[PDB]
Length: 210
DNA sequence: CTACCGGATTGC
DNA sequence: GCAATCCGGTAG
Image 1 (cartoon, rainbow, N blue to C red):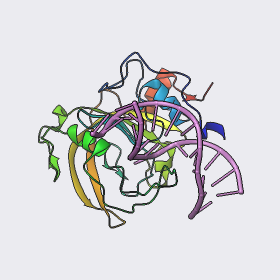
Image 2 (cartoon, rainbow, N blue to C red):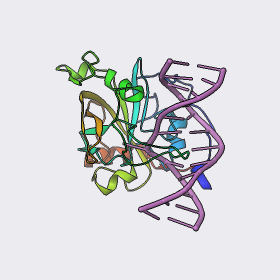
Image 3 (cartoon, chains in turn orange, green, red):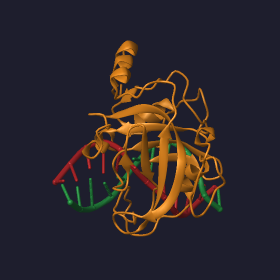
């Protein structure tokens, strides 16, 4: 049973659900054992899903949890995969790819973060820094392939921005939507020495549920 | 490597 | 609204 089925004990209200950018008083480096806790913070509100966004506005946050084999993670930037293209009948939450992904819902949302007009064929922004920001969280299950994944739980790695997005056939040979994200943040990367020394200077530790 | 639940959010 | 979506978590 454990945390498989818990709701939030609390809701971040200090900003609303459609906040782009950092959540005040939640520094880069903050760690949480479980996803529900990350939601409570306001950093990444969806319980389960990879991306938080609205398809007419943008994506606010996302998570690297190694659920999608087409994710490739490079620390300072990375290539994320859109959701969907899966059959979840049977009240499932994850499956392997069984059909082509679509430029809709969160995939559309995240496409809108990119400083260039929405294009059903994908696009790049030349001035990508001027795009709408995305809170990036990394979870310990990216560790199988990524050396940037934390040993446990979830960690907040700061703001990144969608350099470009395009559709393409993934390792499974179904179409997937891919997004190139790149870091633009005021604090160091939690995995670096400097980033690590900063965690310590802030005295951040793993937060567990009360 | 399987199976599947409550709860959070958005789509429309 | 209310139906559809889901990068968890925990059992086996």
